Image (cartoon, rainbow, N blue to C red; front, side, top):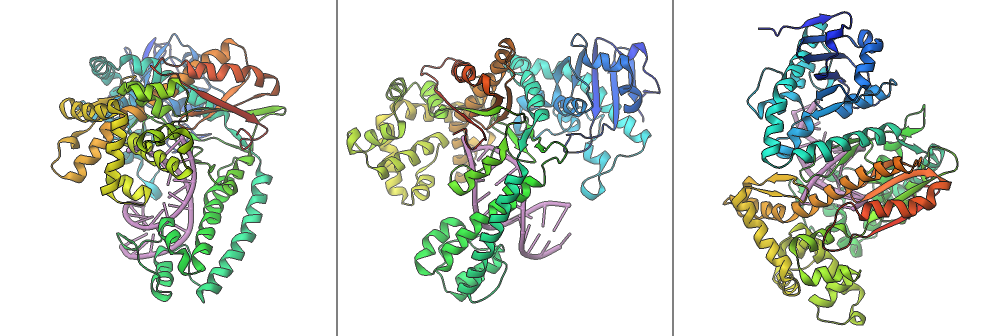
Length: 580
DNA sequence: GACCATCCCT
DNA sequence: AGGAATGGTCA
């Protein structure tokens, strides 16, 4: 039943071949400064299981890990590389990462281990990690005999599956996408994560003090105005005070009871003073739980740093996501919350944070793919696009655009981006579909090319079964041909949206790779810290700011060539907050 | 341990 | 259109 492997107690010369499938196993979910539990190598000479202590103490092994000339096939190499970075070891030569290769072929399958990736091509000579390691309170590294076998099986799997995966990719015209975009990007992310971002804790802790006092005030009020105490954070308990005791109008039901979202409470404010106090409490509460307490809990005390993990093979569109902490949802919209960014600071002395963002990248991508003339023009003029849209759909001159007319031409614009229907717009603008379709009809009259795109795209999705991005990312939409209207329409929104959202991910991903090449060429010390969807955040010495101001937007703006110009803006300052 | 509902970002 | 983290809940 077993798979044959030498359980090596010493590193021999035949374990160091030029081509190999390697496994450096890090069971911990958060791999930052995480133990490596075992190692397996498979190559032309055999199958080997090496204990970390033995192997990682071996100058010959660690030299093989670092040699770029020695090519290694792997599953989720970033996990491996970071875990080794924390131990002063560099991993190079990884020319094939199956996790990223599975992800490119079909992001829907949710590949998250070798077993899942293996089934894709009908190979099942390997177990689901969860099967070996357990789950949750049961998670545990097993004994050496079981471990070594599993690890060798994974390795064997990778060795087996490379050629078939790489062949399919090529058919799909995604071979370069793997080797030139996603894999090279894997390295940059490794470094970004390892580096981390410094957190001024005292600053954070003080904010935690002020909030604690402010929440204590609002809380008391709420109970006073309620004439009672209850768990304000309970959707069920609160829904009893609002909709039963104070007889507030039920404007919405959730699946399990009445809805107490901000949207509902905003409308109920005129009826009772308790409402404003609840929303105020929720705002200050979110900040306390997620942005002061949640953060201080993941700051490493040793370096006062946070090292996020960037998931590269998770999002359905090609975007990244970051975890523990999520450094892509730090509050910026309201001033109270925006001040949480004062706690993100440069890691050295005399350094500054530097933020470069893309200006309306999505809509610029739409302009390019749809080839809409009116829209291409608007961008060649570097116009305010919301004002411009307000001018066209409402048939007025620049000076006639009122603030609300602009607020709505915005709502629509993102409607178009998301492929939204009258109904989605209706609620979004607070109105009715009878009038929401009038805007839409009116939009497509000023933008015949975008209309033309929505039609062609849904149809190609219908015919081909998938939609593609500029750089060849792919999304299968099996639900497009569904008979259920809800399920059909949603797939159509995806057909419409994914090439836009996903071509934007590709572009910034390419930027990131170009930025790295240049930072190195220019011998600048500036290092890339975060990526927030259309934004790159760096920290550099104060001396380098001036060059970065000219260098970063140019590398970004030049990442690809669309029919409309790309436009970047930048800022910098003592803290992240100030990079505004 | 999963779900839910709520809220934060692009 | 894509994501992630929390407290409550009932299990």
